[PDB]
Image (cartoon, rainbow, N blue to C red):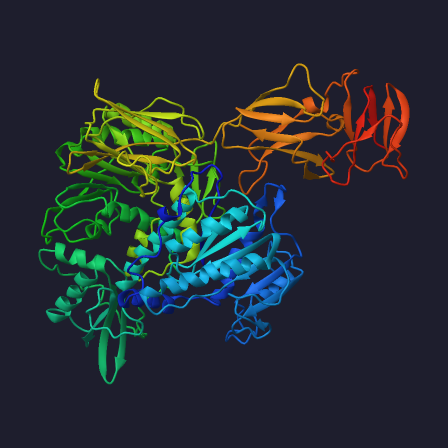
Amino acid sequence: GDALSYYVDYNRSHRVVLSSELPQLPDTYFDGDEQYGRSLFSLARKIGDRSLVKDTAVLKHAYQAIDPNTGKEYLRSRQSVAYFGASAGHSGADQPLVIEPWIQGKISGVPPPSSVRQFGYDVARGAIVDLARPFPSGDYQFVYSDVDQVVDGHDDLSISSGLVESLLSSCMHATAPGGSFVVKINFPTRPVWHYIEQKILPNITSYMLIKPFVTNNVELFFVAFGVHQHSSLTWTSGVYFFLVDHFYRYETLSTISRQLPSFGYVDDGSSVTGIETISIENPGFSNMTQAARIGISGLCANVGNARKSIAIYESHGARVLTITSRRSPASARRKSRLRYLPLIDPRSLEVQARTILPADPVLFENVSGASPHVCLTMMYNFEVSSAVYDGDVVLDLGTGPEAKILELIPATSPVTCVDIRPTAQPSGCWNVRTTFLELDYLSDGWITGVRGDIVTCMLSLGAAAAGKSMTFDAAFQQLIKVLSKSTANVVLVQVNCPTDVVRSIKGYLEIDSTNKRYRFPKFGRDEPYSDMDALEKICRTAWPNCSITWVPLSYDLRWTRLALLESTTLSSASIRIAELMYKYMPIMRIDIHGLPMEKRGNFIVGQNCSLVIPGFNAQDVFNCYFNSALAFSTEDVNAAMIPQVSAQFDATKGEWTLDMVFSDAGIYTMQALVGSNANPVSLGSFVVDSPDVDITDAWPAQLDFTIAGTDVDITVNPYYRLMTFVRIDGQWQIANPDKFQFFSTLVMNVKLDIADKYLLYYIRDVQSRDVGFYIQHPLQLLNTITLPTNEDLFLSAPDMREWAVKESGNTICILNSQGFVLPQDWDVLTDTISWSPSIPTYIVPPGDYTLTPL
């Protein structure tokens, strides 16, 4: 299938970060075992042209970006384009593929450019020049570069990064001022980071990084906007978030592919994932005993719970029964848990009397890809297996008959799978304590005899919630009452509880907002749901010392380790559905013997938030996580990405306090370290909402229509930034840069004009790739400004209409009509004021003026 995309943009509120703090290309990148894993991934990839899927994706982000100084698009229709590194290639296309739809405007959301040029080392239809040196050419509104570096040794990083810096300076001169360019970087290095911040960033206005996911590598793209228009841009923490995930996905995937076999290999049972099969002779006209029974059962012990299939056919005078299946590392952990091999029921394999024609075994069979739900269960499965540790006993709850956990849990951990349907796994031959019991898990008075340490409720509560016509909270309340009797201390639950506004996944998940109900159309499964705040309350009644940690497992490709190693083909579309379907059905972790946490300040983005942490020793250290990463420590503090942090120790009582000012709307989780060996325990989690929408400002009792103007005071959370706009004739326009001046409370300098009385002025937020969606305040006070009769006034026409001015009710000169003449008492101001340079500005003697459009 298609490729995936990851990207970040310059959030203006983030902190200042220096270049050496950002990570770069790992030391162990170019190596023999590294080159194996990447190259294995490339051959197994099923895709058409990789150049087209990468280019159409990154071009789409470039266009849609919004200019604060314009209120509209960075890149304009029918602009001039330069293509660098143009590929004639070997497709027979004789030129880059994306270009011929890009001229025709066949791409959705991309208008045709004016003309396109081609340069490169091996372009067929363009001039062949060395792009690191000057060349005879014009100036372009857009530059696209796909240069690839060349490396044969780890010491070549000086030579390769030298090319990137050289190309950056040439694309600088190539772009006309106010334009844009994009540059692709194969190998991110710290000296590259040092080059970007010092030279190119101060010259540009805004930047964005785009990463498509096609082949398993660290390739990246970088874009610069508004060239030759000096500014004050620096690195941010949002950039740091982008890199740490971008590098980690390579780190996890390199190990996944290293454990896979070579392309076109030969199987003998050695490889951890592979093929295995056996054959029988003369079956179906008697009884299979001894080798027929032992061999067939012994195969099933090695393969486990995976798919199994048979073939029955005749060849060379021999009647054969064939079994083929695919092993996995997961099957290996089931293999050791057995104390000895169990035998099977051979009746079902005997009753056949027809020929089942065989076929060639395939390793990655299902080219259909995993479904979103099959991907969904894998993420839930993994977070359970990684949570369990050796020796810990488990109170498994709601598991289906196939009993997948025996593979998830370690081999030394005894557990029991209990439910309402009899199982199929054999019940006398395991090595450790393994039992199955059939009883309603919501019944009263059963757990008191059961022994367990960790509890897991996976997809179990949801269906029986609809089963007994209850709401989710009531069904959840019954489960809570039972486990309060239980001897266990760790509970992991998968809960129907959205973490965002209710949206229906079109065709995959349809939700009623009022009746708290779910509807899955692919399965016809109907379920109820509950609230995130309330479930916190339910826990607090059962345990005075209970902690909660809503963890967003999404954005972690560890689950894919289960999928790829099990030879279950993944698809891009299924993951994108799966990542969203987690948000509506997250997993809650409860620490029964934890310590309660308290929030005292106001947790709204941009406000001052504070936390209270009692009981910790002066040598103890606190740690914060956001998406399993860490840049926050009481050890460093100053390295924390969020701007304002203060952590103080108070030995008078035994309390710690923390002061935060979060510039991101993220969910943060806490960790605490006790002792010089640092034993970690899980603390609470808190959610910070978007900054206050509210706005309040003061307008002076006596105005000031003079040259120096009057001041206006505004109080806003510092995330938003106010710009002045005018809405005329279905479009939004931006006024003069010097008439309205915003600076630090948010204090205004505003010049007063009579045109303000007849125009309408708005305020919008522009700090993002959007303008005007969260704060949008009209100035009706500027619509009706009282004009003192003794005070001098300015004037400037709103537009070229038949404007007409009457003085105290008496007519004088018309405006915007062929042959306007300045009155015998007015003046022309030095500079134009209105929302157009093509509008002149006049200085008028005091009076009572009335304007009229004709």
Q: Is residue 664 above or below residue 659?
A: below
Residue 218: give x, y in percent of width and height. Answer: 38, 58
Closer to the camera in the image, 190 or 412: 190
Q: Is residue 453 left or right of residue 217?
A: left
Q: In which quarter of the view is residue 110 placed? A: bottom right
Residue at the spot x=87%, y=32% of the render?
822
Is residue 601 at all visible to an observer of this figure? yes
Q: Is residue 450 above or below residue 227?
A: above
Residue 35, horizontal then vertical, whole percent: 31, 67
Quadrant for the C terminus in the image: top right
> How many dots with numbers?
0
- Residue 87 placement (x, y as % from top left): 53, 70
Up/down of 33 relative to 658, above or below: below
In the image, taking residue 390 as reference, residue 55 lies left or right, namely: right
Tell me: 137 left or right of 744.
right
Q: Position of residue 176 (x, y in %)?
A: 62, 55
* In the foreground, 354 or 393: 393
Name the image quarter holding residue 454: top left
